[PDB]
Amino acid sequence: ASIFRCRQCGQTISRRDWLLPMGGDHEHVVFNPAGMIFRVWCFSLAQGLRLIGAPSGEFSWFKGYDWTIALCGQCGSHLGWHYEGGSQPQTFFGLIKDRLAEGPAD
Ligand SMILES: [Zn+2]
């Protein structure tokens, strides 16, 4: 269990080694304006996504960061968000834990 794939299709997305403890925990639980709860895992790095549109600061869950929707690049499943425009780090990924599958490295 060292890499994370898209649960819906298998696309390679990230690695346990790339988990990032933002504010002391790699895990953050948050809701959007529609009341949906997400268990977000922060990653320094991810791949196999497609970042949609341009960044927005509106309702951002992480102070100083602007967000872009991150879809699985293969199947289009909403996997999380890419954060940018902030400080230490300037950028990171917040990925929705239950949308990934963990397993052995390729
Ligand atoms: Zn996918």
Image (spheres, rainbow, N blue to C red):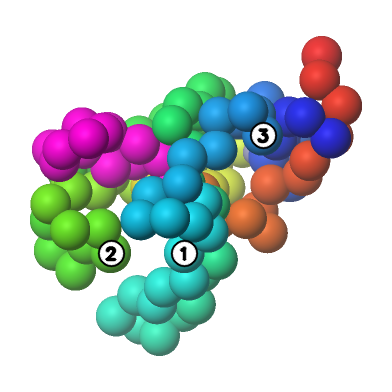
| Residue 36 seen in the figure | yes
Q: Is the shortest distance between ligand 1 and the CB of mark 1 under 8 Å? A: no
* Residue at 79% in and 41% down: 102
Of callouts 3 and 1, which one flags the residue occurring earlier in the amino acid sequence?
Answer: 3
Of callouts 1 and 2, which one flags the residue occurring earlier in the amino acid sequence?
Answer: 1
Decide whether residue 84 is among the magenta residues: yes
In this rendering, would 56 be left or right of 71?
A: left
Residue 55 found in image quarter: top left
Q: Nearer the viewer, residue 9 or 13?
A: 13
Of callouts 3 and 2, which one flags the residue occurring earlier in the amino acid sequence?
Answer: 3
In this rendering, would 96 be left or right of 10?
A: left
Ligand 1 sits in quadrant: top right
Quadrant holding the C terminus: top right
Label 2, on which residue? 61
- Amino acid type, callout 3: Arg
Label 1's element?
strand
Label 1, on which residue? 28
Q: Residues within 10 Å of mark 1 (few under 14, many from 20)?
A: some
Label 3, on which residue? 16
Asked whether the residues under the numbered discs 1 and 2 touch, taking CB atoms below 8 Å apart as contact, a structural biologist would say yes
In this rendering, would 82 be left or right of 49?
A: left
Spatial CA distance of label 1 from label 2 is 9 Å
